[PDB]
Structures are given as C-alpha cells and as structure tokens.
Length: 165
RNA sequence: CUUAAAGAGUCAACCCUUUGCUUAUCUUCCCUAUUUAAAUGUUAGCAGCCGCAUAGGCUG
Image 1 (spheres, rainbow, N blue to C red):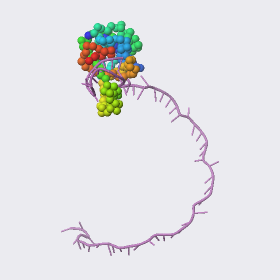
Image 2: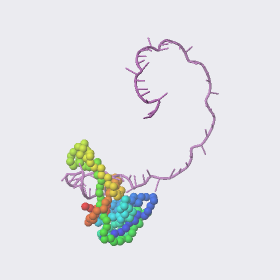
Image 3: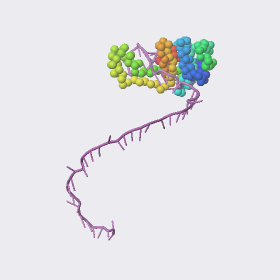
C-alpha cells in the first residue's frame, strides 16, 4: 500500500505537535479522509511526532495535498509517494470522566439527578497516559484531546484518518 | 578484708499594722531602587447514540 510523507519543519516559534494538530484539523474540513485515507506516525515515543504519512489505497498525489495544506506551507515539507507493505494504523479511544456518564444516565434510564450520582459516585475517573492530539471540532464548538493507540489493522477508515472497529 | 562493726529526733506555732513619687521638656536634618525577561510541558484529556453495563464501539 503506497504512502506519501508530510514533514513538519522544526520551528522554535510554534509547537511541533501544534502544527500537526492544525494539519490534522485542515485535513478534516477539506475532505481528504473520505473512507480510505489513513494516517500513521513512525515516531510514537512520548508525543505524536513530526512526520505525517498518509497511506490511501488508491494513492495520494502530491498536487492535491500541497493545496490542501496551503495554510501550513510556512513550516511544512511534503515528500514523494513511496510504497510500504504494512503500516501501523491506529484507532481512537475516548476518556470518560463523571459528567460524561451522569447526563447520559438520566436521559436513557430515567433516573433522578441524585440517583444517577449515587450509582457513579465510586466509579469513573479515566485518565489515559498515552499519546494524544489536540484536534478540536467544528460541528460541536469546543476543543478536546484525542487519544490514539496501536492495534490491528482495519479495512475502513473514518474522517480522522483512523480505523473503524 | 573500707575510723570497718551499729543506732527513729521527734514535737507546736497569727507576722501584722499604716502610707502621695512627684514635678519638667523641640528627635531633627538629607536621600535615583534598578533593570530584564516566551508560560511552558504539545495542555484538557471534551460534547452524544449504539447498547443492560460506570464492558466494548461510533461521531467531530
């Protein structure tokens, strides 16, 4: 499965992962991740990294994504399309923290507010200690941190370049 | 082989009565605080439905 490389140039001004977040945000709103384009990072050590690799099955040409990342050309480097027999695709994992589940339980189970806090008083508090990425959102108006972990491959992809199920 | 050797000090108590420390005053005069820088560690780890699950998935 052929892949192309996107390299974030080293900048003391902006964050290296912060450019990556704006790269991933601009790759979302300008299409790209329709149903087949996936993103892997060769440098999972503690952070996301700096080099971006897109391994779409039909192939990503250089012309389409040099105009997609037109706002990022100050500190980006777009490589040539190479080939790879296997990529390390990742998946999205969410963190649940108290009121994420409190307002869900009163909607479905029909319990009271004090009843819902009683069942979840001595539970929850999930905090992932794994690499994350601060990509925000445009449908719902807030910013958040998205966690990605290494697991098995999947055929289909979502609109974030990650695998589904 | 210790001036070794050894021995009950017990007892009871009214201190107490009185007083003028008073008066007096110039602390004052002077002051260069100063200068200068990244909030970073990616920051916030969110908003809901798919489900019996506070198991596991999706959505941006």
